[PDB]
Image (cartoon, rainbow, N blue to C red; front, top):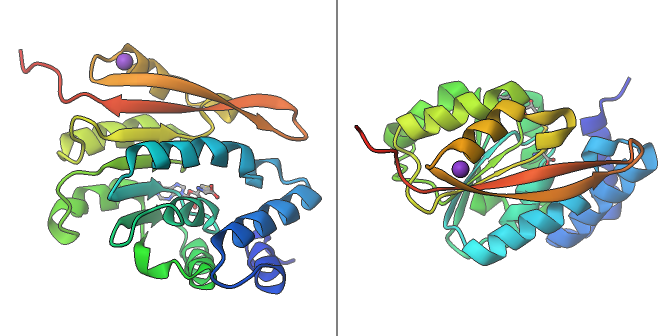
Length: 218
Ligand SMILES: Nc1ncnc2c1ncn2[C@@H]1O[C@H](CSCC[C@H](N)C(=O)O)[C@@H](O)[C@H]1O
Ligand SMILES: [K+]
């Protein structure tokens, strides 16, 4: 049958208002709530995401995992003129839906969808995409890659003192190794935010981990 993804875009195109990102977000959440797709209702985590963007005003954000574009719309709508969101998405069909979602929102010029695996694309950011360092990273892709890709971002020199990592679903289904690393490391200052998931009626969470610069070479 029809994929969740194509149905979410259909619902937006039929119910939301073009060039009104808030209406796009609300339509996605309304539809996903009706379908009882707990991991696709974004308003609770969105409150936390919005507060991060508003506080830190990042000029260059990297997102890992786009899906249908909800979080890309959520973040891009709060970015300044001339700021940039890069979003990495391994599934071309999801990249395609995300692109269409952004076009409907009117936010396509602020976002570049990078089609590929994070582990393959991250080492290309410096030279192929002319990145210095990222201001913010939103981790929302394959859970077992949160820690490896954080280490990869570090090694490739893409983090600076002050870079804000924000990781979703750190409790459900969980990213315990990622949490133990950033919480235990002097290179990250961490804050935890509770975020409810409907139907499962569980308190998931997001972790904010602000990079402090590398550990001493000695
Ligand atoms: N290694 C990887 N690199 C890039 N994208 C990946 C990946 N592993 C999984 N993904 C993608 O990560 C996504 C997770 S769902 C992302 C949800 C989205 N951030 C939102 O808030 O709506 C899926 O679309 C999946 O295809
Ligand atoms: K720490």
